[PDB]
Amino acid sequence: LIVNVINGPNLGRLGRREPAVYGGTTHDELVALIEREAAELGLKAVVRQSDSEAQLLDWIHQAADAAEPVILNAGGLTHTSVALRDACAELSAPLIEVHISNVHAREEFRRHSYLSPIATGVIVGLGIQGYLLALRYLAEH
Amino acid sequence: LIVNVINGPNLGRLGRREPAVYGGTTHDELVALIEREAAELGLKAVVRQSDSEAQLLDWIHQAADAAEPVILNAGGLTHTSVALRDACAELSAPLIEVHISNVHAREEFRRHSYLSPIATGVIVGLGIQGYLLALRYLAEH
Amino acid sequence: LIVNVINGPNLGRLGRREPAVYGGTTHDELVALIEREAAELGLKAVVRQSDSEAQLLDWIHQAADAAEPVILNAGGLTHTSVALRDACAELSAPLIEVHISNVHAREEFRRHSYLSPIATGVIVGLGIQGYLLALRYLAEH
Amino acid sequence: LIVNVINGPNLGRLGRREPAVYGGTTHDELVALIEREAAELGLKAVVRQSDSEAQLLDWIHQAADAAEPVILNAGGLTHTSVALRDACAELSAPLIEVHISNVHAREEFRRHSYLSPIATGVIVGLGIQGYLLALRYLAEH
Amino acid sequence: LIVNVINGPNLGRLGRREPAVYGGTTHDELVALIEREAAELGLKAVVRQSDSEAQLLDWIHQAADAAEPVILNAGGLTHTSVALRDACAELSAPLIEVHISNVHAREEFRRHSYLSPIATGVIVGLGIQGYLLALRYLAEH
Amino acid sequence: LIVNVINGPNLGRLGRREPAVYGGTTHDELVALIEREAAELGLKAVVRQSDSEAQLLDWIHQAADAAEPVILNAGGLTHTSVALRDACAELSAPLIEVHISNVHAREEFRRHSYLSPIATGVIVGLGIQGYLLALRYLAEH
Amino acid sequence: LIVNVINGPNLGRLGRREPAVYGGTTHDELVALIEREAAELGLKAVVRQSDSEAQLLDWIHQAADAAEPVILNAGGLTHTSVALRDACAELSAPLIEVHISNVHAREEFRRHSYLSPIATGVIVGLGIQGYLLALRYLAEH
Amino acid sequence: LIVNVINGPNLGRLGRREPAVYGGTTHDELVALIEREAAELGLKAVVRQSDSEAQLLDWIHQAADAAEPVILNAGGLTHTSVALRDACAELSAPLIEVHISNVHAREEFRRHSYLSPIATGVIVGLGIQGYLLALRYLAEH
Amino acid sequence: LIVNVINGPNLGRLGRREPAVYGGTTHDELVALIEREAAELGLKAVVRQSDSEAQLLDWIHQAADAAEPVILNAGGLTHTSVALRDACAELSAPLIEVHISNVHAREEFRRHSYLSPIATGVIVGLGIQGYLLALRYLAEH
Amino acid sequence: LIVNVINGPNLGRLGRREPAVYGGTTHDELVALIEREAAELGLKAVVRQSDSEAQLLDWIHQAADAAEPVILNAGGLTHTSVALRDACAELSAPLIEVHISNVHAREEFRRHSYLSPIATGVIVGLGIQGYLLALRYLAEH
Amino acid sequence: LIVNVINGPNLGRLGRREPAVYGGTTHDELVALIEREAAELGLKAVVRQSDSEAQLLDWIHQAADAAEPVILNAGGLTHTSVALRDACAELSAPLIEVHISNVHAREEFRRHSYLSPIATGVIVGLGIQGYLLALRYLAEH
Amino acid sequence: LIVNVINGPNLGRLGRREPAVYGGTTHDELVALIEREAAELGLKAVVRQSDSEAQLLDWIHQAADAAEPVILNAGGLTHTSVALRDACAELSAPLIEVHISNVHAREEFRRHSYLSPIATGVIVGLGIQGYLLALRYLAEH
Ligand SMILES: O=C(O)[C@]1(O)C=C(CCO)[C@@H](O)[C@H](O)C1
Ligand SMILES: O=C(O)[C@]1(O)C=C(CCO)[C@@H](O)[C@H](O)C1
Ligand SMILES: O=C(O)[C@]1(O)C=C(CCO)[C@@H](O)[C@H](O)C1
Ligand SMILES: O=C(O)[C@]1(O)C=C(CCO)[C@@H](O)[C@H](O)C1
Ligand SMILES: O=C(O)[C@]1(O)C=C(CCO)[C@@H](O)[C@H](O)C1
Ligand SMILES: O=C(O)[C@]1(O)C=C(CCO)[C@@H](O)[C@H](O)C1
Ligand SMILES: O=C(O)[C@]1(O)C=C(CCO)[C@@H](O)[C@H](O)C1
Ligand SMILES: O=C(O)[C@]1(O)C=C(CCO)[C@@H](O)[C@H](O)C1
Ligand SMILES: O=C(O)[C@]1(O)C=C(CCO)[C@@H](O)[C@H](O)C1
Ligand SMILES: O=C(O)[C@]1(O)C=C(CCO)[C@@H](O)[C@H](O)C1
Ligand SMILES: O=C(O)[C@]1(O)C=C(CCO)[C@@H](O)[C@H](O)C1
Ligand SMILES: O=C(O)[C@]1(O)C=C(CCO)[C@@H](O)[C@H](O)C1
Ligand code: NA
Ligand code: NA
Ligand code: NA
Ligand code: NA
Ligand code: NA
Ligand code: NA
Ligand code: NA
Ligand code: NA
Ligand code: NA
Ligand code: NA
Ligand code: NA
Ligand code: NA
Ligand code: NA
Ligand code: NA
Ligand code: NA
Ligand code: NA
Ligand code: NA
Ligand code: NA
Ligand code: NA
Ligand code: NA
Ligand code: NA
Ligand code: NA
Ligand code: NA
Ligand code: NA
Ligand code: NA
Ligand code: NA
Ligand code: NA
Ligand code: NA
Ligand code: NA
Ligand code: NA
Ligand code: NA
Ligand code: NA
Ligand code: NA
Ligand code: NA
Ligand code: NA
Ligand code: NA
């Protein structure tokens, strides 16, 4: 029923660099697209964004306590934060890691994720439709 | 309209190991699920499997010449074949790389792909629904 | 006389995963155990926890200015934060690094600490008694 | 005209360790020196410091939206934060990375920067005059 | 009740280098301190030292057969001996690894231990009080 | 008073590749700019260039014997010559290492310098103004 | 009762290089020796060779479905094929990996095997008697 | 007299990607150019291409038995196949390895060849004339 | 005729850990099995075990002087001792290295042997039958 | 029309070591062979050799200014000199790198070249005919 | 006056392998040569050999307590023993490390020494005269 | 009879840094000491120094042609020059590599030598007596 979509650092800046990297959809448009899709699927999507690791951790803690699934795009913290990994390892419902860009076609440091080994699955490089596809996985799960 | 789904070595063996690793769906069931989904999406899915790298290359060559999109699960060749990478780099339509298992939760050698850097995107660890989600991306693309 | 016990990200979640990883004592129980032990030793323990690196840094800054000893369990930041290391290098009184779990029996990335080289000493894998043993070292120091 | 000087974790502690590492100038003195130099150059310097990555990111976001140049000394986050790198990659005006100490004469982990590849340039080991020299580059740019 | 304290190569030389590295307590004084503490705790400590790996192995074998806990400071063999690791993996009662010096502040080769992954826990850099603190852990265990 | 500016291999070729890499100023123009700036600062700049390591070493030897400061852009020898490093380690007055290009944005092999650890400081990626900024540091030093 | 002996690329060329590397027995002689030994042991040996990975995979698939033991000398694919590893991981009866030459005395790349971690055991450097010794292990198993 | 030219995976696709990578000559044109050159040199060139490793191995086996020289462009198998290396090590006449593209200017994984250490020589980056130049070496050999 | 079987550290402890790792046969049973097999083969087996490297070296020295073959299971010293390697390099008769467990399925540090490159051959993971199979190789040699 | 052949350190010593490494042709003979071939091709070859990096750089500078092609065998500087690489990157006409010996069959340090990534192409292991084959490429270019 | 010459594992076997590796002088001859040279120099040489690390450590301990210089050829323990390094770090008089063979021309693992960083100096590859040359250094020291 | 002593970059600067690194003997004093010792040994020592690699190479070439032994202290080129290695590999008489300082106690980059693998032997850390000891080896050779 309830799905948490959690976006990390810099994801509030969607639609401000060249559409080359992350597409032309803004974060507000993203929230709207996700909500619309979620309703069609008979889910409720709670979509939140923060540039603060501590805030992200608190959202993951609540999802852990509620046994709610998480779609998480951690931004740069994907590649650097053990703390985020430790919080996500508490989750009992599925965790789908999403990257808008194809990280495997960028710098080598983006090709490692602390989150992938503990996630249910990972979607990269399908732009913002990656979130919609994750919702749909969760609706069937 | 037409989408090629190409499965590589050992994928014909789906449903024969413990459902732990790859799920309980057989390859024939997979073909059927994909075809059914593709028709609902108004696509035609051509689904093929081989344990022979040369056969896989020939299928990729035809997709390149037809400018058709490919959903490719290369099995073990993901981690080892430059030749497959070179064939896939000719593709002008999208290439979505799919892994049934979450390779990031397994041996370290499964965490490298020669295909990811040239793919449009990658879906891992969502089981066979990963193919269905790729079809759906392509139907919107 | 005064000892600061500083816990970092996710340590507020003690007692919520399987007792396998970190034991069944909660953070509030931990505070209570530490305070009781500290009083028996004729010390005052100030025990604080935050998931925010900036808050942790500020607590370390105050300990540096007061020349007070610190028992620090930085959680995931142990393995990732140079900033925390830089703050701890100002400390003139002892710094004892504590890990509840035996990090050497877990993932390889947990086997590196930015803090160990600048700490007085390190206690790992003795569960929450690791804090009590650190207090006792400080009472004799 | 307007230049942002952004200092990251622990830079508020300038003048509190042995003058060996970072010199004897405090952060307030630094702000004053920079402002005085900036006025002589006919610039306005906005100088800000935070130990919070999220706050640093927000300052970089504003500089990106205003197309203003940034002189950035990220402290320990230089060596660890992809998120900071991603925010700085939006900047369209110059980015000069500054380190007070000669990081190349210290620990090996200080010899890598996530920021250098996307900066216009880098000044290290010239103490606080490194900021003044960056201002002067920007006044001619 | 019975605890074995086993010291490896060069530990008989305690109190002969500058107090900088290992302190000014000799091995005989160490035995005496440990015995006194053990009696206060209502334990019996059997404290033994050898520069011979084979002798150390035989002591570990006996502790394994008696199901007795071991506090082990293996000296240089910590970083080099698989054989010692294999003997210690038989132990069914706790194994606490102790280093007098903070190995993390010395040469990089001292930062790896073959023993840590199989030990219950590890205490480093607290000087000879590290042994006393291990005894106290065992008295509560 | 006297400052030596020493340029190494290929720096005589300034202004001959695309202005992309090193700018459009020639070496003769560079000498002129440096001299003009030095006079304004009340310094005398002795500016020399050679493609011969032995000649560079001899210039560094003379600066060492005269206790004169050196601004050194060693070209490709930055990344390869221990001999140059050994000569520069004799210098008792400051050594400022200068790179015209941002080496951190180029090939990985340009990101290591044998000179940085023994230099007073390093300026990269500020083009030829990097020399002028070094002069100004020295005038205040 | 039934044992499959599977030889991979280039093993059909036995007896054609200097007897230094692989001995002077041809593949046909090898088949004959194995059959003779197998009969003495009261086993039936099915001995097959191919330079085609796909053919090797199909033979391993059949052994998996029949629950038959495999003695496998994969030739160069030992060091390179994940696909072969994946097929061999299905085997429920024993898998003995055999190398005629002592791979540990040759190039470093021959010292890694994708098969060893999933094999029951490995025999190297005992020439063709390695096959006979594997048969004998299986006859007792 | 007789020279074998053997092309591996994807070389049948010459002239189908942008002329940037491999030139605009097709494989059929290549065969024709080689034959014409060979006749001028008084040689007979047997030119063959396959995407199948097993087929390539069989061609190398025949060249080994006939003591005929080989010009080999193995495509992606250059970087991945030990089996191909093992077959080529049987060759008693010269082996010239040819790459159309300059592999040293591409991805790092293309800069390693299993074939180079056992080849007589290697020609890279001279396009299809690399084959013609190899023929000419063999005509003088 | 005479074969030396030499077992190193911890091999006297066979049959004392879970049969999972090394089987349920004790060292005395092993000696008996080997002797019985050796007599059937018309050999004399001299079987010795020590936890002392110096004792092992002396046994290898005697085998070198007598030109007698050695079956050696060095235990943990396999992975760590150059001295043992140097002694074994004197042997003129065959040296067969034996491991009871499949070291390739355990920790990565067990996957390197200082002995394999100088051994005639290596048998791993066939339990105690590995010794019997080595005897049989030697009886035919 | 004009082609520069530039030989680096030790190439003046051709014909003085065992013909095993570099052949029996001296440098003077090499000059003569190249000149004769060049005339047959209707080219003029200017062939020069120096053990001085600075002299080599000056020759490359002149070829850059004249837009003349270079055949360069840099000797040991191939593997060590960034300065040479930087000079060769100015060349607008083709650069063919030549090695007489097959560097891939020698020490590992000879398998890296700073020149290959910026060269048009590379010929190794064809002895002195490698120069003649490069001339012929240039005559067709 | 008194100099200790300490030889480690396998050095008692001098003169038993091909004179290629270590020369044809036996250990007894070596003792005699050293004694004769020492007397000519007006020194007393105490020459001892053991294959037991513990015995070597005890000899080093005595040299440390007597403040006597040591010439040490540790054999294979050079490359493997931290314990030996720790004992040698107590020595206050000079420590000269000697290797008979040129370890730099052998396996790569022989090119690392735990002893070199703490030795006064090192002599390798001068055969047994290396000991005589060390004595002579000590006689002048 | 004749021995060449060849000193490389910066060795003309002996006696100008703190006696800590290289001692207080100047190069002229060194020449004098060597000559005096050589005469006592009935040798003639030709002692030469240059900061120019090309000059060093030419001296090594002459020693190769005269079949004269070389004592070589290459300075920083020890760690960086393949060209020097290639010249020294021609030498048929002994080559003794000498370092005044103990390079193993300094930076890690000084612990690799391109010369050691081809030298007869190596003396490090015995100061200038290292040259005298090399002469004496050569007088007995
Ligand atoms: O592609 C993504 O969605 C991504 O997770 C996002 C960011 C930051 C986006 O501004 C980057 O830090 C990640 O490396 C990739
Ligand atoms: O998870 C998958 O789908 C996968 O692509 C498939 C195989 C082989 C499946 O038998 C494995 O070789 C890959 O590592 C992962
Ligand atoms: O064992 C610990 O106490 C530890 O410091 C704590 C955490 C996070 C605890 O939730 C982990 O991030 C550390 O790796 C180990
Ligand atoms: O030298 C600097 O200015 C520096 O950026 C600052 C800090 C933290 C300063 O307390 C360190 O974390 C950096 O490694 C170096
Ligand atoms: O600090 C310790 O107690 C230590 O275990 C002891 C020794 C040898 C002590 O002489 C060293 O070999 C270890 O690296 C650290
Ligand atoms: O950017 C510079 O100034 C630099 O020092 C110069 C050269 C050579 C310039 O032709 C290059 O070799 C360095 O890598 C960068
Ligand atoms: O020694 C063997 O049997 C071996 O498996 C065989 C081959 C190919 C044999 O031609 C090689 O590819 C392997 O590295 C070793
Ligand atoms: O440049 C070549 O000729 C090359 O051998 C060919 C291929 C495949 C060509 O489609 C690539 O796989 C090689 O890396 C380079
Ligand atoms: O499997 C074996 O026989 C083995 O040689 C034995 C030991 C020690 C056995 O107690 C281990 O040290 C080796 O790694 C593996
Ligand atoms: O093979 C060659 O031509 C080569 O370029 C030449 C030399 C020096 C030749 O004396 C070596 O330094 C190179 O590694 C290989
Ligand atoms: O060359 C030597 O003297 C040496 O120290 C001796 C031995 C053992 C000699 O049998 C080897 O273990 C060392 O690697 C080299
Ligand atoms: O110790 C030596 O003699 C040495 O060869 C000399 C130099 C340069 C001396 O100024 C250094 O470059 C070497 O690393 C060490
Ligand atoms: Na919620
Ligand atoms: Na991970
Ligand atoms: Na999209
Ligand atoms: Na199709
Ligand atoms: Na890749
Ligand atoms: Na699924
Ligand atoms: Na406090
Ligand atoms: Na560290
Ligand atoms: Na506890
Ligand atoms: Na502003
Ligand atoms: Na980077
Ligand atoms: Na300053
Ligand atoms: Na006991
Ligand atoms: Na370990
Ligand atoms: Na203490
Ligand atoms: Na001057
Ligand atoms: Na350095
Ligand atoms: Na500029
Ligand atoms: Na069968
Ligand atoms: Na593996
Ligand atoms: Na055999
Ligand atoms: Na043919
Ligand atoms: Na290779
Ligand atoms: Na061409
Ligand atoms: Na015997
Ligand atoms: Na080895
Ligand atoms: Na068994
Ligand atoms: Na010319
Ligand atoms: Na390169
Ligand atoms: Na030739
Ligand atoms: Na003595
Ligand atoms: Na060391
Ligand atoms: Na000798
Ligand atoms: Na001479
Ligand atoms: Na080398
Ligand atoms: Na001296």
Image: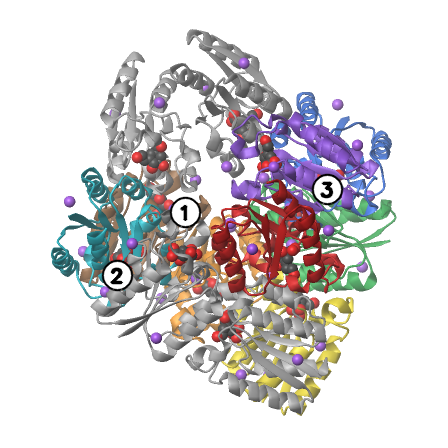
Chain colours: A red, B purple, E cyan, F yellow, H blue, J green, K brown, L orange
Please state which of the two labelled residues, at mark 3 or mark 1, is closer to the viewer.
3
Q: Quadrant of the N terminus of chain H?
A: top right
> Position of B32 compared to A59: left or right?
right
Q: Amino acid at mark 2?
A: Glu
Task: Using the numbered discs, state the Cα–Cα distance from disc 3 to disc 1 in whole angstroms.
Answer: 59 Å
Residue at 80%, 49% in the rendered image: J35
- The answer to which of marks 2 and 1 sits earlier in the sequence is 2
Q: Is residue F9 above or below residue L82?
A: below
Circles 2 and 3 on the same subunit = no
- Left or right of K106 in this view: E101: left
Tell whether circle 2 marks a residue whose Cβ is less than 8 angstroms from ligand 5.
no
SS of the residue under disc 2: loop
Mark 2 belongs to chain = K
Is residue K11 placed above or below H34 in the rendered structure? below
In this rendering, does residue K26 appear at all?
A: yes
Find out if the beta carbon at label 1 lies less than 8 Å from the nearest ligand 11 atom.
yes
x and y, in percent, of residue E30 in the image = 16, 59
Residue labelled with disc 1: K110
Q: Residues within 10 Å of mark 1 (few under 14, many from 20)?
A: some
Q: Which residue is mark 2?
A: K90
Q: Which mark is residue K9?
A: none
